[PDB]
Amino acid sequence: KAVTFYEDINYGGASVSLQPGNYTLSQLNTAKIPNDWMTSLKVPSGWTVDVYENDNFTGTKWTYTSDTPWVGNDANDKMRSVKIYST
Amino acid sequence: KAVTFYEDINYGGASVSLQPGNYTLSQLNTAKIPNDWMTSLKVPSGWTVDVYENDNFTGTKWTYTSDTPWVGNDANDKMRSVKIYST
Ligand SMILES: [Ca+2]
Ligand SMILES: [Ca+2]
């Protein structure tokens, strides 16, 4: 079980999987996730993904609790930090 | 659906709408919300707005879960950071 983040719409392009945790921009980059890059994601059942517009879990927050082929026009290519929960 | 913050009592004066997220003072300013300015707000049903006296989600916290024509004497013109939840 992991959250997989995808570069392109409908789970296309480059992908990176992450376990639960609170990942800053620098930490995302080390995990090979660039800024302003995420477009779709797969979320395990029962899990929560809080996607933040700015670093350090600030700015607009978009929340996903299931597989999402398109994050929305506002959220597209905006992720700079993320909190992942298995609850 | 958005939280709309208003300059004056009873939803008067300048207004700015924000999606869920954790907004610092600088982020509020970029969204055109000055410090010590907010007097009333509209909150979508089921949402929570935590209004903080100081930057970075510290100091006194005032909580609103419905449309509020007057934030209260203590809370008036004090917002410097805010957390908005759709839950
Ligand atoms: Ca993309
Ligand atoms: Ca005011």
Image (cartoon, coloured by chain):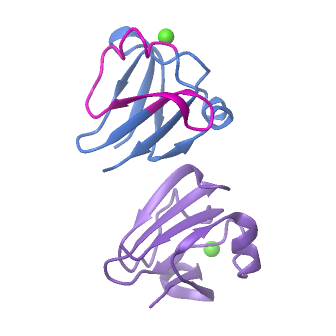
Chain colours: A purple, B blue
Foreground residue among A2 and A76? A2
**Quick check: B65 left or right of A17?**
left
**Quick check: A12 left or right of A65?**
right
**Quick check: B52 left or right of B35?**
left
On screen, A70 above or below A17?
above
Which residue is drawn at the image coordinates 45% and 13% (left, top)? B76
Foreground residue among A55 and B57? B57
> Where is residue B24 drawn, in percent x and y?
62, 38
Q: Can you say which quadrant of the picture contains the N terminus of chain A? A: bottom left
Which residue is drawn at the image coordinates 69% and 73% (left, top)? A28
Which residue is drawn at the image coordinates 38% and 36% (left, top)? B49
> Where is residue B68 drawn, in percent x and y?
30, 21
Q: Quadrant of residue B73?
A: top left
Is residue B25 shown in magenta?
no
Which residue is drawn at the image coordinates 33% and 40% (left, top)? B48
Q: Can you say which quadrant of the picture contains the C terminus of chain A? A: bottom left
Foreground residue among A32 and A85? A85
> Where is residue A41 drawn, in percent x and y?
49, 79
* Magenta-colored span: B51-77
On screen, A67 above or below B13?
below
Q: Residue furthest bottom?
A: A1
Is residue B62 shown in magenta?
yes
> Where is residue B15 drawn, in percent x and y?
47, 22
Disc count in the image? 0
On screen, B30 above or below B47?
above
